[PDB]
């Protein structure tokens, strides 16, 4: 149990933009595309947690951290963004750009 948590943590802490996704997931794809549209590829990690023997443990931990077990699950500098709909709200209302500017990721 500790092992799974430590592995998830490492992904979130070693990558400024961390996205947990699954196979053939339209809102995963959309969210990742939005983020790459800010040229964040170099600070981005996408983990497919469906292709993983411990998917349920990972999803349960992501729910403990964020309130939902669904993918996509999106972290920016360890802060919880949430899912694709959360990302879209932040993007449309200017908060996403604000976040990225404070990190030096967008001018
Ligand atoms: Ba399918
Ligand atoms: Ba990368
Ligand atoms: Ba298993
Ligand atoms: Ba199992």
Image (tube, rainbow, N blue to C red):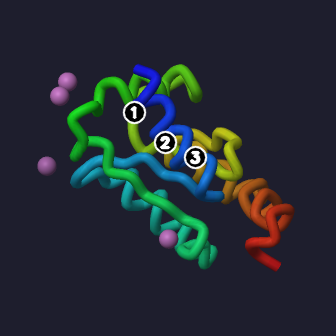
Q: Residue at x 57, y 75 (%)?
A: 42
Q: Quadrant of ligand 4?
A: top left
Q: Which mark is residue 70?
A: 1
Q: Of label 2 and label 3, which has the lower sequence position?
A: 3
Query: What residue sits right under mark 2 in the picture?
Result: 73
Report, in whole angstroms, how far the alpha carbon at label 2 lies from the one at label 1: 7 Å
Q: Which mark is residue 39?
A: none
Q: Quadrant of residue 67?
A: top right
Vertical position of residue 17 compared to residue 73: above or below:
below
User: Could you tell me residue 36's position as x and y percent?
Assistant: 53, 72
Q: Nearer the viewer, mark 3 or mark 1?
A: 3
Q: Of label 3 and label 1, which has the lower sequence position?
A: 3
User: Could you tell me residue 69's position as x and y percent?
Assistant: 42, 27
Classed neighbour count for the residue bearing mark 1: other residues with Cα under 10 Å, few (<14), some (14–19), many (≥20): some
33 displayed left or right of 21? right
Q: Which mark is residue 12?
A: 3
Q: Residue at x 82, y 60 (%)?
A: 98
Q: Secondary structure at mark 3?
A: helix
Q: Tell whether label 1 touches label 2 (CB within 8 Å).
A: yes
Count of numbered circles on the image: 3
């Amino acid at each position: 149990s500790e092992a799974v948590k430590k592995w998830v943590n490492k992904i979130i802490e070693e990558n400024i933009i961390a996205v947990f996704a699954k196979t053939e997931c339209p809102y995963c794809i959309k969210a990742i595309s939005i983020l790459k549209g800010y040229n964040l590829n170099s600070h981005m990690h996408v983990e497919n947690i469906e292709k993983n023997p411990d998917m349920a443990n990972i999803q349960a931990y992501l729910k403990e951290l964020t309130g939902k077990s669904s993918v996509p699950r999106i972290f920016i500098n360890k802060d919880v963004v949430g899912g694709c709909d959360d990302l879209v709200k932040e993007n449309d209302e200017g908060k996403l750009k604000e976040r990225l500017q404070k990190l030096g990721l967008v001018n």
